[PDB]
Image: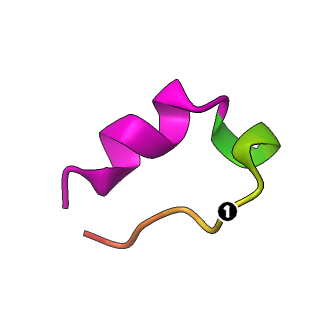
Amino acid sequence: GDAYAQWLADGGPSSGRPPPSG
């Protein structure tokens, strides 16, 4: 899913959330 694009924008792992799968 497009959630990964936002996940990286939030600093990736730094954000404090699991990387979306699809």
Q: Is residue 6 above or below residue 2?
A: above
Which amino acid lies under the numbered mark 1 shown in the image of this protein? Answer: Arg
Which color mode does the image show? rainbow
Position of residue 3 in the picture relative to residue 15 (left or right):
left
Image point 77% across, 55% down: which residue?
16
Q: Is residue 21 above or below residue 14?
A: below
Image point 31% across, 54% down: which residue?
3
Q: At which x and y percent is residue 7?
A: 49, 44
Q: Is residue 8 above or below residue 1?
A: above
Q: Is residue 1 above or below residue 10?
A: below
Q: Quadrant of residue 5?
A: top left
- Provide the secondary structure element on which disc 1 rests: loop
Quarter placement of the N terminus? bottom left
Position of residue 7 in the picture relative to residue 5 (left or right):
right
Q: At which x and y percent is residue 6?
A: 38, 38
Image point 64% across, 39% down: which residue?
12
- Residue at mark 1: 17
Q: Is residue 8 magenta?
A: yes
Image point 51% across, 34% down: which residue?
8
Residues in magenta? 1-11
